[PDB]
Image (tube, rainbow, N blue to C red):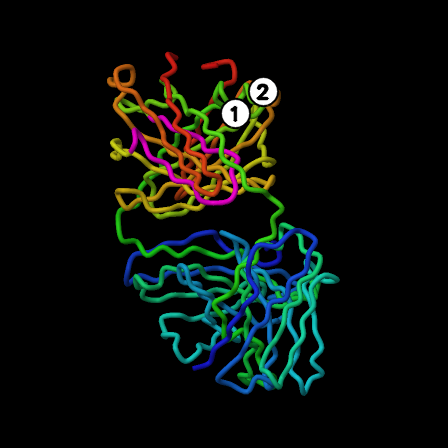
Amino acid sequence: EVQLVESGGGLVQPGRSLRLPCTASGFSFGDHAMSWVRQAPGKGLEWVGFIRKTTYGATTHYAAAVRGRFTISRDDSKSIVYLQMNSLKTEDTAVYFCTRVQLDYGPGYQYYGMDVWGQGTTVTVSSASTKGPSVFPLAPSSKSTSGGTAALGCLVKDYFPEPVTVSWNSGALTSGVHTFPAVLQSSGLYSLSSVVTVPSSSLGTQTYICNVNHKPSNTKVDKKVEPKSC
Amino acid sequence: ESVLTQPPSVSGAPGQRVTISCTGMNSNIGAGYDVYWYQQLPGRAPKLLIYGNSNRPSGVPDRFSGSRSGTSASLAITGLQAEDEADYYCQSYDTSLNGWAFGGGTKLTVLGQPKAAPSVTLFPPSSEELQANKATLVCLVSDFYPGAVTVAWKADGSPVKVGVETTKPSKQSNNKYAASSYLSLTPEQWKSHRSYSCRVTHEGSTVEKTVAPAECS
């Protein structure tokens, strides 16, 4: 089986260096050019760079985003290609894929498609520190009532790292609950929301409390959400 | 990217035929550089789908085909199957960038349930948050299919793009989809404007929600 195996992933501080080794097996490593591609969370593929095969000089070329910061090298005797990341910034955060450049011959020239892909390694660049969340009420009102049922929630804001869990009324209320995935704000902190649909008739008779648990900081927060009469 | 553009999402029923367009420029596809296509199944790594505009690797079924006309390329899936749900990416060399450029990607949905228009709820910054010198608007989208959507914000009618954070859809209890978007401001920015809007685009129709700082304080 033809395989590519990356390693070196983890959380690293902005401005530091990290080396990603990629080990090849099941094919003549020296006969192929090797190429690195990355993918930021929830985003598309972005080419990082590539190193030519040994018979063509092992020269390298880099994408403009990483030129002057990242380098690439190969060791044919160990069947490894490296991505040496230097002077890392928050927007280098991505999954890093090691890929092989094909040799399939076309009409007078060879193609250069990326025909084998590793499973990737996750590199995270962040300077954030552990911090429990702030829980804010999403107060229901006429503006959040869509004919009989009203929506109400809690905004779990400014926490690090993931994850949090949200329950309602200590897990007694489950019907109508949707908890959303978190966003990552530019400050480096996460924020998510949990909203529940309840009947408007019971808004002033039944109490609604959201229970937020952020184990990485040993905080639990219960917040009572009160209806706004407007 | 900008040099290679794809529709964010396309959908079709099983057995039908859909196309994903890769719109290039004269510095890449128009110049005659070959087009490549990659398929990324959910939670998996990309795999080579089409190389050299039209050739298929050994383990790629013939329902996939690719062409290119001048400055654009196309990927055709003739006979959609449920396992074809994936992100699809096109790729070409670009002489301007001197590098390997990608399209932004296209989410293919293989329709397995009726399409659903989305529901939207816009919550204002809470009193509790404003007292902490913070302000966030929460826009929650729910009950839509296929699981693709576009969120845009406006302040006083004019678009606003700074401070926007949006998640990707996820399955709900009824196997539909939901997503969320945030607009972060200062308490002063909030109070200064007269209206804010969340616009949710889905299947060529847009649903818009509006909150007012003077109302429900």
Bounds of the magenta segment: A151-170
| Percent coordinates x, y for residue B212 in the rendering | 50, 19
Q: Which mark is residue B196?
A: 1
Secondary structure state at the residue bearing disc 2: loop
| Percent coordinates x, y for residue A18 in the rendering | 64, 62
Residue B206, magenta (yes or no): no
Instruction: State which quarter of the image contains the N terminus of chain B.
Output: bottom right
Q: Amino acid at mark 2?
A: His
Q: Amino acid at mark 1?
A: Tyr
Q: Quadrant of residue B43?
A: bottom left
Residue designated by label 2: B193
Nearer-the-camera pick, B177 or A130: A130
Mark 2 neighbour class, 10 Å CA radius: few under 14, some 14 to 19, many 20 or more: few
On screen, residue A211 versus residue A183, left or right, reads left
Q: Residue furthest right?
A: A68
Q: Which mark is residue A58?
A: none
On screen, residue A52 versus residue A198, left or right, reads right
Q: Residue furthest front?
A: A218
Marks counted in the figure total 2
Residue A160, magenta (yes or no): yes
Query: For the point 44% across and 46% down, which residue is it?
Result: B168
Identify the chain of the residue marked 1, using the numbered disc in the image.
B
> Please, is residue B122 above or below residue B100 in the view?
above
- Give the overall secondary structure of the magenta segment: strand
On screen, residue B79 versus residue B33, left or right, reads left
Q: In the rendered structure, are the residues bearing label 2 and label 1 in contact, judged by CB atoms less than 8 Å apart?
A: yes
On screen, residue A63 versus residue B44, left or right, reads right
